[PDB]
Image (cartoon, rainbow, N blue to C red; front, side, top):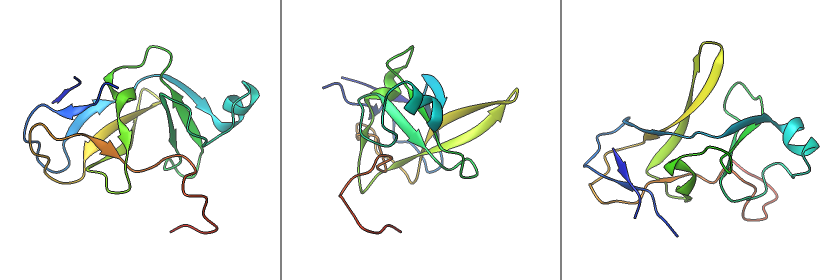
Length: 123
């Protein structure tokens, strides 16, 4: 369970590891759609989540449109949560899960999803 007091998403309760926290809702686009709409893929637009872990198929969720409190989640190199996917009725949904236990009143963060650090390589 979560809570947002910019606004910051925070654990409402001492969550256990691997706990479903919140769905990242918004408009789903493949990379090509995002680029056709005029935006650059994996550059840090506010309220946009980039996700590449569904079998290498690059997509994003634009939460300027009917998003929820999940759009407020900040990125961190030391995150306590992660984006996971599931298929429901042939539609992909993205959810934020805890990576380990999260004390109540701790900010919920996920790993950087956009091109940060200006690196030559990545792991």
